[PDB]
Amino acid sequence: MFVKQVFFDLGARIHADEARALVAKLLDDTQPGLVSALMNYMPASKTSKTEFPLVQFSNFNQGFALLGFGEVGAQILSDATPIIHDAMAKLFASRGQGVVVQVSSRDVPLSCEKRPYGLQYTVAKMVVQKKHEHRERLANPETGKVFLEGLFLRSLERQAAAVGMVLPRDLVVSFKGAERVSSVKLRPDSTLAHGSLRHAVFEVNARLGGLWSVGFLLSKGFGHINTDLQLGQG
Amino acid sequence: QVVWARRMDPILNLGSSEDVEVINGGAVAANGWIQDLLANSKANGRGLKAFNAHEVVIPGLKWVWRISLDRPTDAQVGLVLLALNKMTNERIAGGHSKDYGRFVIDGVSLNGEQVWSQSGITGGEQYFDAVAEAIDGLSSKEFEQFAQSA
RNA sequence: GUGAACGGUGGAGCAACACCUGAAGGAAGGCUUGAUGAGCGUGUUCCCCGCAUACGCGGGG
């Protein structure tokens, strides 16, 4: 259907995972149901859900941003916005002179159509390795290529299934190359790290008309970009 | 032409709190108005920031106006030409703030004869003299028993 | 064999002449189409969830 994008401006850039950690800490004391819905927690305990994250953070040049996929995530985002905005207002008025928190909103629709010609899409900060077997597949390009093709196709399929719209199942994908290889950290000052691709280029015969999320670590603002910008971006 | 005019909410365009120090109560009230408009955006009290179009006529085109009279006295014609001398201060439109309605009279035909110049009307001297004799002797009394209802 | 039997309500005639719905009345007053999204950090085995039924697959932080 549609995905709603909420932009939060504080005058300074904070990273999406750091904003996720910061957002949880300020509201930990009060209103726990709002935090449970925002982070996609299970309704009983603190453990997050296994399924597709409806609410995820993203990147914003002067702050961070929220993505709510579908009507449920849009409603969760709709009820979350004033409490979170007041939380940054009190947090940034507690210290310093004070800064005006500035909000923005968009309701981006989602669409997909199959075309008989290849189309190019580039994704930045792409996490691909999460067990040892995926590290073994990444050593040889032939057996890592088909793994990446299946990962991209299953990512598109699970996002189409979670948003509630039908995706044609005759899509063919192709992967050209990635600019860099870098690690990501789950928590700061932790020895554990996950391998990741940087500026990866993919080619799909079909076209996409909105925000699309691919791969793992979707709730940390990793590996989603606006396709509607990328039609004819060059 | 379809000409587009929009509003913003300028408190949605503040940015710097040094601009907000003019607003009494600090930045917390401005942030409350931010929270009011986002609460309106998720959800019939209108806020601000509209986007509208209005169709206007193009500028620079030439029009014709017809002001006719039914057995006029020369003083009435003189009053019409006194209005036509300084028409150009007033505006032949609505849209007062957008300057809409500015015009310059190219010509004035007095039963077909052209009397218009750059410095008002050149001609019709009997009508002007008649209206100059009509400003004299003009009291509010005629207006009062014109407006008085039986 | 009906106190019946028989029997034209007809002919002619102008609803029409005259008569002004409209005299007066401001679409107005305010309003950036320009913002938002398209570039910058992490280096290796550890908690939860399902299918199985552990030979492993899937996902998730």
Image (spheres, coloured by chain):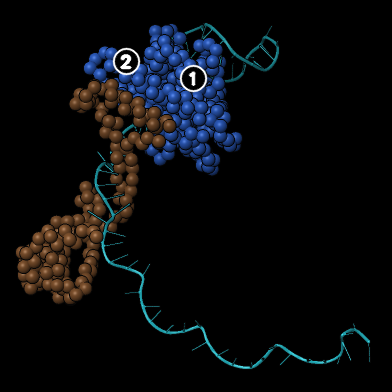
* Tally of marks: 2
What chain letter is assigned to the residue under label 1? A
Count residues near mark 1 (Cα–Cα under 10 Å), then give few for <14, some for 14-19, many for 20+: some
Q: Which mark is residue A37?
A: 1
Q: Nearer the viewer, residue A232 or B24?
A: B24
Image colour assigned to chain A: blue
Q: Position of residue A160 (x, y in %)?
A: 54, 31
Against B109, residue C25 (above or below) is above
Q: Position of residue A8 (x, y in %)?
A: 35, 25
Between A86 and A176, the one lying in front of the other is A86
- Residue type (three-letter) at the residue carrying disc 1: Ala
Q: Depth check: give the residue in front, B9 or A73.
A: B9
Q: Badges 2 and 1: C-beta atoms under 8 Å apart?
A: no
| Residue at the image point whose x is 38% and y is 17% from the top | A19
Percent across and percent down for residue A204 are 51, 35
Give me the chain letter of mark 2.
Answer: A
Q: Earlier in the sequence, mark 2 or mark 1?
A: 1
Instruction: Identify the disc placed on residue A182.
Output: none
**Left or right: where B57 falls relative to A126:** left
Classify 10 Å Cα crowding around label 2: few (below 14), some (14-19), many (20 and above).
few
Label 2 sits on a secondary structure element that is helix
Question: Closer to the camera, A183 or C8?
Answer: C8
- The C terminus of chain A sits in image quarter: top left
Q: Quadrant of residue C24?
A: bottom left
Chain seen in brown: B
Residue found 47% across the figure and 31% down from its top = A3
Mark 2–mark 1 distance (CA, rounded to whole Å)? 22 Å
Q: Is residue B28 above or below residue A187?
A: below
The residue that mark 2 highlights is: A91
Q: Which chain is cyan?
A: C
